[PDB]
Image (cartoon, rainbow, N blue to C red; front, top):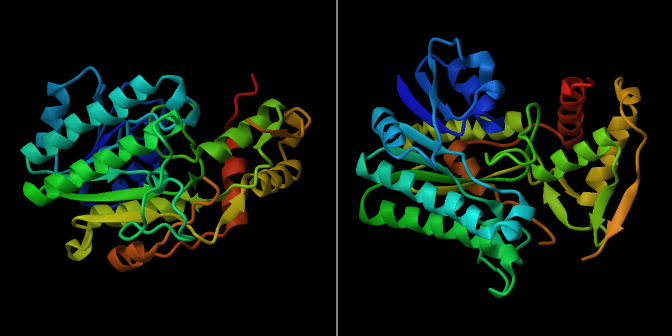
Length: 332
């Protein structure tokens, strides 16, 4: 069976991907992280192996597992917006430098790497549909620190593309668009995966704080149920016909589009009608605050390379992600 190394497995994508692979009979999962609370249900599984580790501290221990495995998925990164500008140097040392080491182990040992790039790479691209192969990337002046996350991830994509071109590194890059469902990552966890926007709004509802709408909350985003999203990540791992080699694939549901304001409304509506509503404080309302306007993905590469098409409707994802969250909260 194919050995899949998940770096930063203790989280949203790690949980769902693991469930998926183990469901199959030809995969061996090595989940590396500093903790396992989020994937404890798998610790006893015969084909799951927890590996104590940290990509910032361990050098050798990780290089070892890269050589021991077949496919590598680096999920450790700081993707929370505040942090970009808050502690830029850390975001750069972890997201860029540490991940580069791992990218390099993959080329050294000729392993396949499935790397999570970001939709932020497109920046303020004017295309209505962000295309992995044709869209230009637009960012602000350097005096706008907000873009350091975007440009860093973008440089990594280029470095990977360079290794694939000059050193035969086998790879596939994927760009997730607001993945959501049960088991969302903690808002401050350095594991990429769950949509931060919906995690934040649900927290607002759960804690009784207002839903901040920046400049009206008119910016639009696309939401993807994790059942759809993880199904695509799964096929990238399958790599039928090797169609994913050297590819950059957007993974999101372009039909689930909503402004932050509408998202807040749908969430609130589903919240009010929920059985456990009474255990949460009263809604604090929407606060308009004023200190990227659209992010719709082209999914032609996913159709082509994966024969994938998102099947879950917006409401369904909304209701299920909120439901699971509310029933998981520790009221004491």
